[PDB]
Amino acid sequence: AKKVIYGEDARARLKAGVDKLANAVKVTLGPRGREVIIEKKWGTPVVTKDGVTVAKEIEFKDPYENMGAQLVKEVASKTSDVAGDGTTTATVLAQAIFNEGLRAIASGANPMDIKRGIDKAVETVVNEIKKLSIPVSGRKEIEQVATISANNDATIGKIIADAMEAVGKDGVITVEESKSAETTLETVQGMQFDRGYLSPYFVTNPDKMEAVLEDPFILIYEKKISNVKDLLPVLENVVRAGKPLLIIAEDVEAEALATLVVNHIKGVIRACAVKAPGFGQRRKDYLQDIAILTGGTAITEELGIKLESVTLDMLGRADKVIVDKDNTTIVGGKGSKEAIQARIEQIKRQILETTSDYDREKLQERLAKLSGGVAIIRVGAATEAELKEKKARVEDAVHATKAAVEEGIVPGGGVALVRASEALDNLKVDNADQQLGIDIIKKACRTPIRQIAANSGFEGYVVLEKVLQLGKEKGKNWGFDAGVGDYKDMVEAGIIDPTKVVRVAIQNAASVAGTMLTAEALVAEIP
Amino acid sequence: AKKVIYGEDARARLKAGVDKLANAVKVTLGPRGREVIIEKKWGTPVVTKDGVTVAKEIEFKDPYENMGAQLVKEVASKTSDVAGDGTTTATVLAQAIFNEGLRAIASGANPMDIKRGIDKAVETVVNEIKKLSIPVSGRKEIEQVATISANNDATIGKIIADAMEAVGKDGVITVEESKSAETTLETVQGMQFDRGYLSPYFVTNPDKMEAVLEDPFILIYEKKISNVKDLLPVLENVVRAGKPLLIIAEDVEAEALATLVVNHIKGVIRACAVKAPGFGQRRKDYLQDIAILTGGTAITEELGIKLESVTLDMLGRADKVIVDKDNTTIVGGKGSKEAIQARIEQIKRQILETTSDYDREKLQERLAKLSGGVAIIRVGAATEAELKEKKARVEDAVHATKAAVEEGIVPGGGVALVRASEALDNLKVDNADQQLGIDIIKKACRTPIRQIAANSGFEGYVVLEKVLQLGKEKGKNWGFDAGVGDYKDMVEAGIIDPTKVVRVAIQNAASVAGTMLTAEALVAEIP
Amino acid sequence: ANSGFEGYVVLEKVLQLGKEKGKNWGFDAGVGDYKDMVEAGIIDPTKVVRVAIQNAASVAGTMLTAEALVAEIPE
Ligand SMILES: Nc1ncnc2c1ncn2[C@@H]1O[C@H](COP(=O)(O)OP(=O)(O)NP(=O)(O)O)[C@@H](O)[C@H]1O
Ligand SMILES: Nc1ncnc2c1ncn2[C@@H]1O[C@H](COP(=O)(O)OP(=O)(O)NP(=O)(O)O)[C@@H](O)[C@H]1O
Ligand SMILES: [Mg+2]
Ligand SMILES: [Mg+2]
């Protein structure tokens, strides 16, 4: 059984649902925003300042108020997926657009024309933001963006700035929970994977459980090694060279492995055998990456080269390999620069499509493995409750730092939307109702700065008026520093946020709020 | 369906939840603290004085009050995991920080700045505690620490002091329930495991049921022995030496075992065979630990030596072994007294990284087996109900004794926190709200001493004033002896607790309590 | 407690001042400090203190051993 409600009754339900969701999220906005404790059915409650985390939990008993809440939750969800930051700003913007749109509709405006006017205004606002955008000069902007996104935490900003330099432009940064109270940065350069150490007898550094080979030969072969007859020819010729030998396969069984280890103990060869990483389809690409990095080729099942007939011609080579209990690293063969570049070009071309289908984001890691490096930031705290909140802030700053490199940086503290909203004064349209939609965006763009002031104990309208006039007297980058409560140049002070975050937040907020305003009836099941 | 509460209503719920949990735990604090009986659904109720045990059982009907209770339970849980003692002190500290933080916030202070001020004060307090820390000189402090942590039980302190000396600096102490009413200490030196006595006919002393062998040869072979054709060649050469032979194998069955027992009865050899300890990978390392201690080499499938091809060259040796119905003990390998130090260093280097992996002392047991010994304290009482509480106190004193060796000892009775809080008078910060956070820690650090006095029937504020003034008139170590009710030197009187416990308690209490103070809204499901 | 101080803390210090200073030393509630009561003029007739404790103990003892209460049913 369904019930349908119409007109002002329908919009009243939607407004109540949107307001109750937005009121919970908006308390976390700004440098003086406060956190929200979320009940978890099993275990410790979650304390968080993250906007999308709070929004994802909200749900209401009233079927019609819930519909309003669930629509605005999409604003925070989409912003997190695309930018990873600005979810609270997007939620604040969505409420402002919806609330002002209802006032215009209540005056008799056409709901569809308001949406058309809103779309035109957002196109102008996004263009203005890109004009204010400044490309990241280097470490100074990176450390400033990380500090601001981490809720003004210079310790986190320093670590992320170091991580960006270590892995470079094409590297990847991963955030994990440390097992101790300290927060550490761990960087590894070159190829590595989660396999190795088929037997303890390959020890070369007993003080560290490390198997170390210098200028080793790398054997990339798919299937098992299960007998001496085929393993001997590969061993029969590496002895002549005298260089160390490394074996990568799915496994080496007892009859096969006992040959090398009894040979390794006597020192006729210095070698080690490791299992090939991955499963199923995901095998060949890694070994192909490993083979192309080593300057040799991968012995492939499709290739048909019998293990007996192999030689030193296609045997791979590296400079240094380190093997431990569960990990092996290859420094690099520094070969095939153009060939790997094609895979780098292709993988990123595949990423933009495979990101909607892959099981894990490790496809990006495949790019970084043969072209850059990976950095692991292990967040640590005295307790689990503090660690969860600290780790979330680090993830937000990592995402914001990545977004800043792509599209530059913009004045923070909500100044960018205030500056962009000024151009809407010159945007005139012939339709009266579409003009109301433009006016809605102008008021909405100036809402985040007022909420930041309100959270810090200042009047939003007083702060907004000063910031508007300071744009003419001092410059476009001047704003309000809610941390200490005075006006200054935001870009010089380091209060900046990425252009991508600001652009995505206004676009997502307008798309949902504009769609909701066109509604006239709500259909929901009777409880 | 969620409901969100804000501001003072939210903090009122949290304070009620924290207070109700803390009130139950705090009755167990001090030498005159009393016990709590916890209902168990099936069986006898549990009577305990353990702070974390009481905290773990607390749960409330109100979802918002339960949120406060579950967060503070993390303070007691983390303290028990890290130090094993001081869980009641940590819970008392957490309530004091949270209660005083709410008062500051109600006056208009910024919650985030209070947390920053709290963090600075804890850093100073921890530094001061390490200044007061005195390293453990020997048995005198070990007995004093064990006695205090066992609730002033001298008999328990004596036993633990003996156990520490027996196993040495690198041994391990295990607490178990005795089958009788007496409490006994049992110490064994050297390697031992839970296998042995494949056949009852291997008897050297029929009075005591064991198979003592003098200067035996130890045969470390991984797989099964199941034929005469391979056992006999190894038997062909042990007879020449005339020394006894010990077999460690996967399983000796009828056909293989019948050879020795018939031969053993005839007296041509004196030998015994035992089960190999462990399963899976836990097999591999154990015989490796046995092989290195005995001076021989383990005959693994990996090594590549067949059973009939073995000889005296790699056969292990020992001075004397004891094998009984369920235990085999090797008392001395007479070799590799230099190699094990490298092995020892390799082990704890793995131990610290595998602290995330292990859930049983087997990680340290293997290290303790070869480098030291193990001591089993079997707690006994006339009744199961009394035994449960007595065993808990013994475990607390064992953990405290271990923690005292690591980081030294500090004046007890809450004096250390009082002395450390004095340095907070000199700590000034530029932000007014951060100063309130420092003042919160100063009051919190002086709460445990007042609660100990309150449990003993004295006035806490009167006791605190005297202890503060005695710090300069008499010395820093002077405090209040709540057991008898007079002031004296705590270090001379033996009222001391480990530095690690005091440091861990304040750090865990501040991390959780500081995090909760930044909360503004609570999201919980409607019941 | 009525004046805004902890009752047991005040009582404990008044007991201490009974032998450090003298028997007449107590706590002044008009201004929160300890002083000699007789010199300060904070004195009571000894009949009041004597009769109050005697009267209070008499009624309390009567009610402690009361075994039955007889009253009319309110309609
Ligand atoms: N010191 C400051 N003074 C003024 N504005 C600031 C300051 N620090 C940060 N901001 C601004 O405050 C906003 C950041 O607050 P934050 O709580 O991260 O909002 P969000 O990014 O929209 N949500 P989340 O997904 O939770 O990070 C941005 O607009 C910053 O530019
Ligand atoms: N005779 C004593 N006089 C004064 N203080 C004492 C005395 N004995 C112990 N204490 C102190 O009282 C505290 C020990 O009480 P205890 O009940 O063990 O607290 P906890 O260790 O925080 N909780 P638990 O985990 O249950 O042991 C420490 O601060 C001791 O220094
Ligand atoms: Mg952010
Ligand atoms: Mg204790």
Image: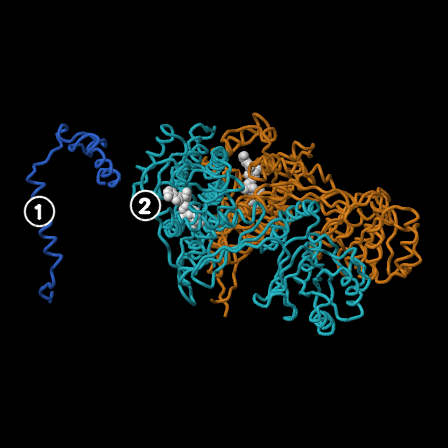
Chain colours: A orange, B cyan, C blue
Could you tell me the amino acid type at mark 2? Ser
Task: Report the amino acid beneath label 1.
Answer: Gln
Q: Which mark is residue C54?
A: 1
Residue A163 higher or lower than B50, as above or below: above
Indicate the chain on which mark 1 is placed: C
The numbered disc on residue B451 is none
Per the image, label 1 sits on a secondary structure element best described as helix
Give how far across and how far down residue B524 sits, in percent: 46, 55
Label 2, label 1: how far apart the Cα atoms are? 33 Å
Q: Where does the image place residue C37, in percent across and percent down from the top left?
A: 15, 31
Q: Where on the picture, by quarter, is residue B423?
A: top left
Towards the viewer: B104 or A320:
A320
Residue at the top extreme, as displayed? A473
Residue tagged 2: B456
**Residue toward you, B257 or B344:** B257
Q: Is residue A458 above or below residue B73?
A: above
Q: Is residue A340 left or right of residue B54?
A: right
The chain letter under disc 2 is B
